[PDB]
Amino acid sequence: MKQYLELMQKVLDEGTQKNDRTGTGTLSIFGHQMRFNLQDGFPLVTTKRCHLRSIIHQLLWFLQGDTNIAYLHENNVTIWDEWADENGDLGPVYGKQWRAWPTPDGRHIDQITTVLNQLKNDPDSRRIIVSAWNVGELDKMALAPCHAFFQFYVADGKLSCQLYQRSCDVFLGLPFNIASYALLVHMMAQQCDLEVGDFVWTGGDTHLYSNHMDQTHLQLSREPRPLPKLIIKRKPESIFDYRFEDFEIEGYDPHPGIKAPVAI
Amino acid sequence: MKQYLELMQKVLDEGTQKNDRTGTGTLSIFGHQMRFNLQDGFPLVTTKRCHLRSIIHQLLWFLQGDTNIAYLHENNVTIWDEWADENGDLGPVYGKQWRAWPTPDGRHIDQITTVLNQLKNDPDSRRIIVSAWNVGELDKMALAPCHAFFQFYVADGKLSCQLYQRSCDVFLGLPFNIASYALLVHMMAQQCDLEVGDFVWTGGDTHLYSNHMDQTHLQLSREPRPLPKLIIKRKPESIFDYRFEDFEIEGYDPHPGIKAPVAI
Ligand SMILES: C#CCN(Cc1ccc2[nH]c(N)nc(=O)c2c1)c1ccc(C(=O)N[C@@H](CCC(=O)O)C(=O)O)cc1
Ligand SMILES: C#CCN(Cc1ccc2[nH]c(N)nc(=O)c2c1)c1ccc(C(=O)N[C@@H](CCC(=O)O)C(=O)O)cc1
Ligand SMILES: *c1cc(=O)[nH]c(=O)n1[C@H]1C[C@H](O)[C@@H](COP(=O)(O)O)O1
Ligand SMILES: O=c1ccn([C@H]2C[C@H](O)[C@@H](COP(=O)(O)O)O2)c(=O)[nH]1
């Protein structure tokens, strides 16, 4: 996508070499925002083939409030296996925070039902937020949340979403996240009988790892193609009842996949 | 300031009319970002006169862990009175979350001291974050956090900060908020012997209130004057040790004040 390849080049041209936690090295910038008008097409990168199976099962996993990779496993998704403990868990990661944030006094708050009731009952609210950054449980988490925080907005019947991402690996993880949250805005918009608007991505430390340098070069030389269109094939009676079969992506003619090693 | 005045012009050129919680009516855009290089000058608006007494005092109150207005009152700062209860209390807002976020296992996390340890011992961390958005306590808060989350970053011995403001009142609140976080970056950097980098502001619902349209156009007709300079006269043993008197702003000549109503 033009904005995405412009962020790749930006990093390449201005990033500073930093030693990172892995000991691989990064080239990074701090502060970047991208806007994707969703009316114009689905933001799935077309300069490399992106595979939806993982994107979709991971979002449905999250909305279930499940932090154990068994479902993911049962659906052939491997992305979280490195971080999961001895018997499948990640501790209170994304889905537990989304569906059951623990109050200090023992109650649990369901930020996705809150956000649903806010979109139907109070759509002009300036507080339609879901936060995964639970400072009090970060220590029990296999990995601190990368896509930490997000905010919805309604104006002239359209639903927009801004995501704050504290840490971003441009080559591998950024295409994944952009699509994931663009997909949640379409699910969220359908349930609330609403139009889709903008997806705004904002990042903190945005970086390209030293061993993805050739792959970036290879991806930057390809021309972006027309964006696909997402088809949602049936309306559930809740956001919690969507299934993998419900989604279809028409128009996606990508350049071939580029493989690149993960720095863990 | 060029950046601030361009944002106001943008809200005026691209905003949608939206009704707010206080029913006064706003003009809003969703998603903006702007960067202020702190080496260029101290970002206090000059197209209208700002009073620095309250920017410093509120920030020391926050760093104290305080959420009761009495301190602010004896330094006659009345910016928080409209929201405080009978006993001066605001409930667990900024100062309490920053200095003692309550966990579900009995602990409390001092997020400012943690940030300082990270800048000293692990400055390349992508996790140097302070969040006031505590979902399990928002119902005890007198007002939900508008400046909800901020991230620090250290590159070439320069400290930068990125603030995410979920709701922004552009005429009243935003000159207060930019000056407050630029102060904290200078204080942090002084304590850690770092130079100042950039303060990067990102907003969610960024808006102008309807009863502010004339004051905004008045402001916009003015030329920015050269930015002031911040001189700190002491290096306190800790960041919790600063006094009002340790700060001096040099060469600040603003255009006349412009007065305007608060929506409560
Ligand atoms: C992001 C995320 C979830 N994850 C992992 C993952 C890792 C660290 C994290 N760290 C943090 N802070 N939060 C997370 O949500 C998180 C998630 C991913 C893992 C691998 C690939 C990946 O290598 N993609 C390959 C192909 C495989 C595929 O299609 O799945 C590629 O070529 O793109 C993508 C996403
Ligand atoms: C941000 C922030 C902190 N705050 C708290 C705070 C809380 C709720 C809010 N609600 C709304 N609608 N807008 C805000 O800017 C806002 C700000 C402020 C409170 C008042 C003023 C204000 O009226 N100041 C006068 C100056 C005179 C004085 O010192 O009293 C002004 O004309 O600007 C500014 C900031
Ligand atoms: C809140 C906090 C601050 O210091 N600065 C701000 O600009 N605000 C503003 C935003 C909005 O005008 C109002 C809060 O209303 P709501 O909670 O968003 O509904 O104060
Ligand atoms: O949604 C995601 C998930 C992970 N990552 C990457 C960012 C960093 O490369 C790493 C997170 O590690 P720390 O920043 O906590 O060190 O995973 C992303 O870019 N996006």
Image (cartoon, coloured by chain):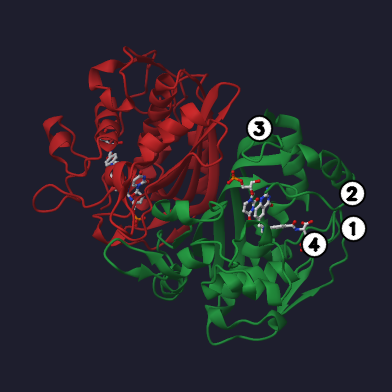
Chain colours: A red, B green
Question: Label 1 marks which chain's residue?
Answer: B
Q: State which mark lies toward you, 2 or 3.
A: 3
The CB of the residue at mark 4 lies under 8 Å from ligand 2: yes
Q: Local crowd at mark 2 within 10 Å, few (<14), some, or many (≥20)? A: few
Towards the viewer: A8 or A160: A160
Find residue B50 and name its label. 4
Q: State which mark lies toward you, 4 or 1.
A: 4
| Disc 1 + disc 2, Cβ < 8 Å | yes
Can you say whether B1 is above or below B230 in the image? above
- Asked whether, in this view, residue B171 is left or right of residue A111, the answer is right
Q: Earlier in the sequence, mark 3 or mark 4?
A: 3
Towards the viewer: A173 or A26: A173
**Residue corresponding to mark 1:** B255
Q: Which residue is painted at 42% across and 39% down in the image?
A: A217
Instruction: Calculate the distance from the C-alpha at mark 3 to the C-alpha at mark 4.
Output: 28 Å
Q: Earlier in the sequence, mark 2 or mark 3?
A: 3
Residue B147 in percent (x, y) is at 57, 54
Q: Local crowd at mark 3 within 10 Å, few (<14), some, or many (≥20)? A: some
Element under disc 1: loop
Q: Which residue is painted at 73% across and 37% down in the image?
A: B10
Specify whether residue A65 is in view. yes
- Asked whether, in this view, residue A182 is left or right of residue A21, the answer is right
**Residue corresponding to mark 2:** B222
